[PDB]
Length: 537
Image 1 (cartoon, helix red, strand yellow):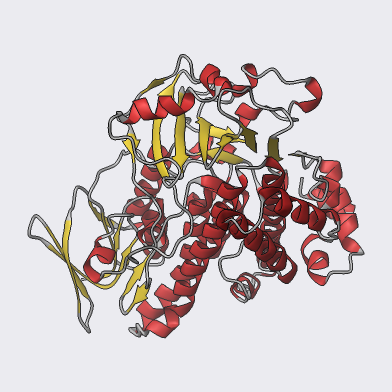
Image 2 (cartoon, helix red, strand yellow; image 1 turned 45 degrees about the vertical axis):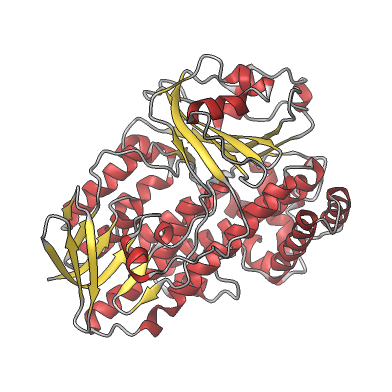
């Protein structure tokens, strides 16, 4: 009999498995597929980097820290990955060239780490290998037919007639989660307000958008678009270009390409093949057309229905429904992996405690469920707001700076807790992250929640016909222009600054600006000396 059985041998399960095996527990990993296999969730974001570093230090699994840097990924995982220096956004209208004044770029600050485009095939193989090396058992090509809970544990039954017995079950697979299937955990219909379906593949021969747009030098981004994740924005949808070969001497010539479409505005086209639908959208936008002219798909296309789903419950006695087994929003802003990490960080230390006390009372896991649902609700709001804003660039502009400034602030929040735990050797400083009033919000501060609430009511009113996009953009731009907290040295409070470029000098200015700031949270999270900022470079 096992301590824990984990369903799903992707990153979510194998990171969790790696922790529990590293601490001496008997782990079984179950998955219906075999490695290597393709998987989605390619961009990594700053919060992902800092929370990977966090769980790596907190739980003593060095392999996890290797995903937190582009250079460590290339040196320890495989050479097959891309770099992610920035998020790039570009607006397109049907038949028209892209307007160079309707772009956004967020260059990721160096302090949070160097981000990457994960070739998930190789990261997930890496983590699976690490899990087995720590002691996990694994059954691949294993189809779960039945889950049974009693007061002594859980029994998982597979199609081949074998049986796995454990004290706890974690389902970390995905949409086809057998635990959600058994227990009817999926909410029908979903409570989620975001609607989007998908068509995606990997391609070879995709060009850089930098080489196919005619942009005046003064509107060209500080760093190349192709050096990060390109988001081609259009009405109620967006396209991603995620290269794995955007750096010198890259070995992987592939590029992840996909399109998200609001199915209420873009109903299904069963008369077309998935590829034909994809190209029908590409042909609407001539710059995208030029960028993808010689590109060829190397996989069987995936076309989905509405991809959003959510669950009514996440924990039970002797079980936990984790990350993508519980819910999904959109690939936009790459929240999923970050969410997975935050959950593992919160679940692991709890599960271990339960296991060594044979006390599986659901109350001890109540926070995990709260976190899960909060993660999903806030993520929903972030993406839905964005999709609404895609109709009108000046409204999107406010969405953009509100999201990205919080990226920086929350990243420094977690990083500060991490460094200070590394200096005092006291885990309290990491556990204080769980005392936030807004579980799931990336920036759990009152002024940010107010700003985000206001953004959300305006965007939902625009979606409902009660307010025009122009009016909401006017109101939000006023709020942004009269705000005092939006890292002005980086330009977040300037609506005419579209390319946020956090250079070293600006970060220094942020620290000085934060030192004598009236808000206590700004002072706590960003006030440094120039020495401290220069030291961590």
